[PDB]
Length: 255
Length: 255
Ligand code: HEM
Image (cartoon, rainbow over all chains, first blue to last red; front, side):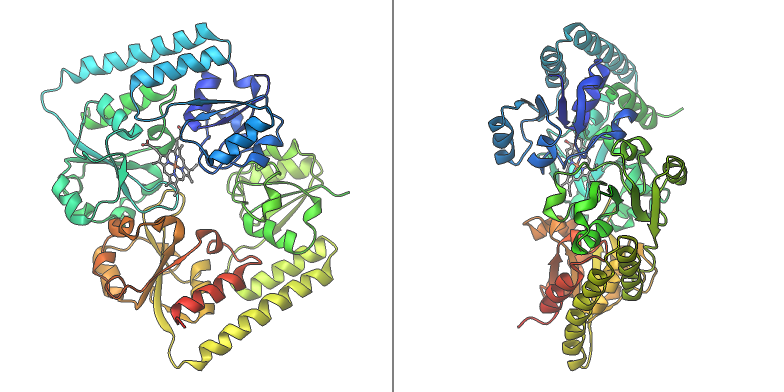
C-alpha cells in the first residue's frame, strides 16, 4: 500500500491518473507512461514476472492482471507476505475497465478519484458514439499486431484492440478469438476496407509492411487506407483510451 | 568497491563471464542474462537511457554502446562525475568482439580473464569451422526475425544473425545490408535450403508463421527445413555465441 509494484502498462497509467503514482516503486516491461516511470526499475513482462526483480524492491503490494504469471511467482510473492492484487483483463470491455478503476481506487484508498476518472472517460466516449451515429457509412477494419518477437497476428474478439476499434465506430471483420496469424488467403477473405497497425511496425516506411502475408492484395492497401497507432495505446485500456478512440475515429472518417 | 551500471545485454554477459560481475549494481532492460542479474534493477534501454534512473544507483562508471543515447544523458552522467565507457557495437565481427572484450577486461582490471574468454570462444568456433570446411558447400540459409514490434524482416549482411549463420557454416542468401522486409515474391525467389526463425516466434505452433509473406511457398517450408533458435542469442555477440553457433551447426547438418 505504501510501496507498490505494478505489472500491467495500463494499470500503471490508471494508478498515476488517480494520484497514487507516488507509491509506485517498480513497474513492468509494458509500462512506458507516464514519463516519471522511466526512472523506475522495470521487472519482466507481466507474463514473465521475476520474483527477485520484484522482491528486491521490498513492495507492500503487487498489482497486476489475473492472467499474469508465472503462477509460482505469485505464490512466491504471497509467501513473502506481499499483498497481490489481480484484476480481470479480458475480455476487454468498458464495463470491466470501470470495475477495475473502482477496485484499484478502493485498494489505493482514493475512491473519489476513481469515480471522477470513470465519469471523465465515459463522457468523452459517449460523445464519440453520438458523432459515430452521425456517420452515413460503416467502416470494415482490421488491426494487425507484431508484438515482441511474434509473427503478425490479427486482433479478434475479446482483445483490447477490438474493443477500441469498436468504440471508434468501426466494424472488426475478424471474428476469431483474441489473436491469430492469418495466411494471405484468410486476410484476402477478411477483405478489410481499412487496416490498422502500430507505428512501430511502420516506423516511417509503409513498405516494411510488405512482409505481412496478403496485405498488399487488400483493398485497404490498394486504396491506401492504412492507419498507424502507438502500440501502448492499443494494447491496454488506460486513462488515455478516449484520446486513442477519438484519434482513430478521426482517421476512419477524416477531414 | 566500484559500482557499475551496464546498458546493453551483450555487454552485461561479457562482464559477468569476465568475473567482474560482482561490481555491477544496475543494468538496462535488454539485459536478461545471467540469472543472477534478476535481482538487479533494470532501468531504461541503451537506446533510451534514464539519467535519473542510472544516477539513483550511485554508479562510479557506466558501460554501454558507442551509439547508446540520448547523447545528452551521457553528458549529464559525466557532468555528475560518472566515468562513462563506450564500445563499438558495429560491425558484428569476431575481431571487434574480441577487441571489445579486451577493452572491457582492461578497464575492469581483469586482462587475464579477458584473454581466457577470447581463447575459450575462439577454440570452440575453430572446431566448428573445421567441421564446416570438411563439407564442400555451405548450406544456403536465411534468418527471419520480428523484434521491437516490427514486421518480419530478413537478416542481411552486417547483422549479428548473419555473423552467426556464417560461423555455423551457412551461406546467407540475403545480399542486402542489415534487416529488410521481404515480399512473398522476394522470399520465394531467394530460395534458401533452410530458414531459421526464433523459438519465441514459433512458440509451440509452426502454423503461427503462416502470416510471414511467402514462407509457406518456400522450398524450406515444404522440405520441412525450418530451424529454431532462441532470439536472446542472435541479437548480440556475447559469451554464449559458441553455444548457439554449435547448436545451429548441428541443425544445418543433422547427425
Ligand atoms: C513475443 C512476445 C510478445 C507477445 C506474444 C505479446 C502479446 C501481447 C498481446 C496479445 C497483448 C494483448 C493486447 C490486446 O488485448 O489486444 C499484449 C499486451 C501488451 N504488450 Fe505485448 N507481447 C509480447 C511482447 C511485448 C513487448 C516486447 C512489449 C514492449 C514493451 C509489449 C508491450 C505490450 C503492452 C504495452 C501491452 C499492454 C498491457 C497493459 O496495458 O496492461 N509486448 N501483448
